[PDB]
Image 1 (tube, rainbow, N blue to C red):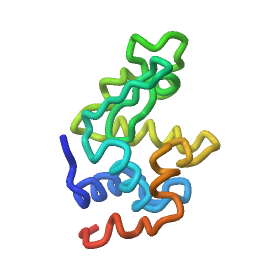
Image 2 (image 1 turned 90 degrees about the vertical axis):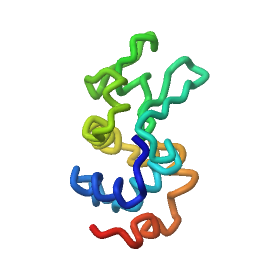
Image 3 (image 1 turned 120 degrees about the horizontal axis):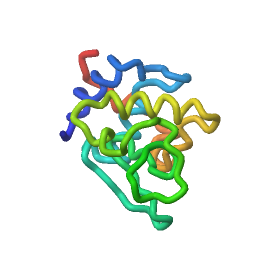
Length: 129
């Protein structure tokens, strides 16, 4: 499913992402925009053989099991396919674990390079939240 900007803001807010670990809702929406263009089905292969899945492009090397990333840990305890669902719950719960592991949202390259230090509030401007 391809989310609309406000539709995703609303769903993320409902899932407790607004201000989770100090990161306002605008940060998450911005990250989703640049990581997957709001598409829950996005996948991208990395040079190391691992793959990124879903709206938040979670990696198979550490977070989920896709059956083809040797020696990977399944820290979120879920098949990577669950992260491609129209229901963002699995992606949200796993992201909360990632953002809590010490590096914050810096774990998301697009966030660090395209959202960090920008006016992230603009990503939720106009949405009835």
